[PDB]
Image: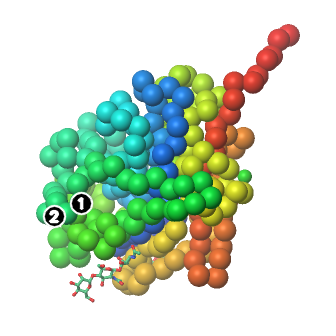
Amino acid sequence: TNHQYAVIAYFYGNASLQGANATINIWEPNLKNPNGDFSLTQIWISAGSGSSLNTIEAGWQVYPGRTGDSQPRFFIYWTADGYTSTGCYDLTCPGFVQTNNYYAIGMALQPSVYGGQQYELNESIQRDPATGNWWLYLWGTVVGYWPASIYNSITNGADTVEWGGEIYDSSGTGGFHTTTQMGSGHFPTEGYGKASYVRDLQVVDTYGNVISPTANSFQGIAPAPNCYNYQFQQGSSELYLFYGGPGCQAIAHHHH
Ligand SMILES: *[C@@H]1O[C@H](CO)[C@@H](O[C@@H]2O[C@H](CO)[C@@H](O[C@@H]3O[C@H](CO)[C@@H](O)[C@H](O)[C@@H]3O)[C@H](O)[C@H]2NC(C)=O)[C@H](O)[C@H]1NC(C)=O
Ligand SMILES: *[C@@H]1O[C@H](CO[C@@H]2O[C@@H](C)[C@@H](O)[C@@H](O)[C@@H]2O)[C@@H](O)[C@H](O)[C@H]1NC(C)=O
Ligand SMILES: [Cl-]
Ligand SMILES: [Cl-]
């Protein structure tokens, strides 16, 4: 694959989670190859596996080939068969039902300032137990829902939630030698105001309580750690996932 990640994953014993939150620091990462590159930060809420993988996805993405510019834009995605034949971005296919247009799916977002003003995308996803519909709220305002009727394995709840950053490297370096940025383009050790974060790492358990997992409850993923990485910063108030990085320069020079 030509995707790279700095992602954490929360796995539950069964598909009974009832929702999750994500409050995602907004940035405008730079793409080295805008013809096909993209960079994003999102939540993935899933059940099943293989061709029965169902996902619920919301975040921000810089993807010029899809959106027509390099601004961070709010996006959604879903699939009901592990990305084989079903699912699509935003409202480009029948799927998500938007009930409130106060916020536009695809809207450009305000990017944070290095060492300055920070902006957050707060999204809350909540399963309605009477229907199986999954409702989306942004900054506390309803947008709409993913209907249970498009799904097969996530209608009763989810078994996995993932948060963090992703880049797609269209130049074929495997995401290992591209200066396409993830998050703010800065490594997590730079911390608040300089490296991007996800907070409100919360799930809704089977008993309906809101639970903020501790850091040891997460499986981390960073397959190109010299290029993009994550670091937990567990404060007293809440757990922070700091994530991203500048990418790696094409500095290799090997010869026999
Ligand atoms: C983090 O996730 C939790 C869990 O989904 C969010 O709390 C939930 O927020 C929704 C809508 O903001 C609450 O819905 C309201 O509930 C009352 C009944 O008490 C109902 O009459 C209202 O019409 C409305 O639908 C819901 O109660 C609440 N759930 C729980 C378990 O607390 C929370 O908003 C998320 N926070 C962030 C920052 O994303
Ligand atoms: C799903 O499983 C629940 C209990 O599962 C275990 O306990 C919770 C607290 C987590 O630690 C989880 O990872 C474990 O597998 C049951 O109480 C619940 O009824 C189950 N739901 C269904 C629909 O069967
Ligand atoms: Cl899978
Ligand atoms: Cl680091």
Q: Which mark is residue 160?
A: none
Mark 2 crowdedness (10 Å alpha carbons): few <14, some 14-19, many ≥20: few
**Residue ID for mark 1:** 103
Residue 92 appears in the picture as rendered: yes
- Marks 1 and 2 in Cβ contact (< 8 Å): yes
In this view of the protein, which residue sits in the foreground, 46 or 22?
A: 22
Q: Assess disc 1: are there few (<14), some (14-19) or many (≥20) residues with their C-alpha within 10 Å of its C-alpha.
A: some
Q: Residue 77's spot in the image, x, y percent?
A: 31, 48
Residue occupying the far top of the picture: 256
> For this rendering, which residue is in front, 230 or 103?
103
- Of labels 1 and 2, the one closer to you: 1
Residue 123: which quarter of the image?
Answer: bottom left
| Residue 100: numbered disc | 2
| Separation (CA) of disc 1 from disc 2 | 7 Å
Q: Quadrant of residue 149?
A: bottom left
Amino acid type at image mark 2: Asn
Specify whether tag 2 is near ligand 1 (CB below 8 Å). no
The location of residue 50, given as percent across then percent down, is 40, 44
Residue 156 seen in the current view: no
Tell which residue pokes out farthest to the right in this image. Answer: 256
Residue at disc 1, secondary structure: loop
Q: Residue at x 75, y 24 (%)?
A: 251
**Residue drawn at (48%, 79%) of the image:** 211
Residue 23 horizontal/vertical position (percent): 45, 66
Q: Residue at x 34, y 40 (%)?
A: 83
Where residue 41 sits: x, y (%)?
47, 51
At label 1, which amino acid type do we have? Tyr
Quadrant of the snapshot with the C terminus = top right
